[PDB]
Structure formats: C-alpha cells, structure tokens
Image (tube, rainbow, N blue to C red):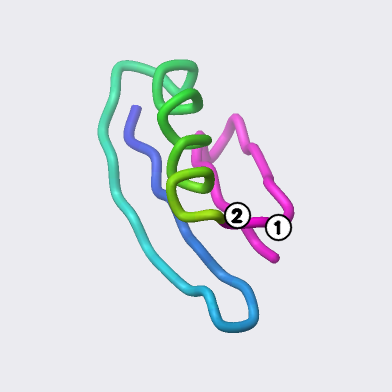
Amino acid sequence: MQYKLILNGKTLKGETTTEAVDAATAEKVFKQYANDNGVDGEWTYDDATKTFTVTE
C-alpha cells in the first residue's frame, strides 16, 4: 500500500516517500508532486510495485 516517488532529470533530482490506503489515492496527490515541483518527464506505473516515479 506504500508507494515511493522518485524525481530525476538533467538538473532536477528528488526522492519521496508516502503512505496511503491505495495508489488511487496516492496517484492524485502524487501527480501534485510533479506539478508542485514543475517536473516534466515520463511517468511509469507498476501494479506489482505499486510505485510511481517520474523520469525526464
């Protein structure tokens, strides 16, 4: 139920950790992380790893 947020890019790197009931809940807030951190990259979603990460 725990998901991790990783931020990469050229000069933009960051790591995050959050806990929720499900990814559906984390997904909405997670997207805010990128938006909150004007991050523009590629997003991936794994059901087995229920983890969200953004790579530019």
Residue for point 46% across, 54% down? 37
Q: Left of 49 or right of it: where is 9? A: right
Counting labels gives: 2
Q: Does dot 2 land on a helix, a strand or a loop?
A: strand
Q: Which mark is residue 10?
A: none
Residue 31 pos. (x, y %): 52, 35
Q: Left of 43 or right of it: where is 49? A: left
Circles 1 and 2: CB atoms closer than 8 Å: yes
Residue for point 48% across, 73% down? 13
Residue 6 pos. (x, y %): 47, 59
Q: Distance between the residues labelled 1 and 2?
A: 6 Å
Residue type at tag 2: Val
**Residue 54 counted in the magenta span:** yes
Disc 1 target residue? 41
Quarter of the picture holding the N terminus = top left
Looking at the image, tell me whether mark 1 or mark 2 is earlier in sequence order.
1
Residue for point 57% across, 35% down? 48
Residue 28 pos. (x, y %): 48, 23
Q: What stretch is highlighted in magenta?
A: 39-56
Residue for point 70% across, 57% down? 41
Disc 2 target residue? 54
Q: Does dot 1 land on a helix, a strand or a loop?
A: loop
Quarter of the picture holding the C terminus = bottom right
Residue type at tag 1: Gly
Classify mark 2: residues with Cα within 10 Å, few (<14), some (14-19) or many (20+): many
**Residue 2 counted in the magenta span:** no
Residue 35 pos. (x, y %): 52, 43
Classify mark 1: residues with Cα within 10 Å, few (<14), some (14-19) or many (20+): few
Q: Nearer the viewer, residue 9 or 5?
A: 9
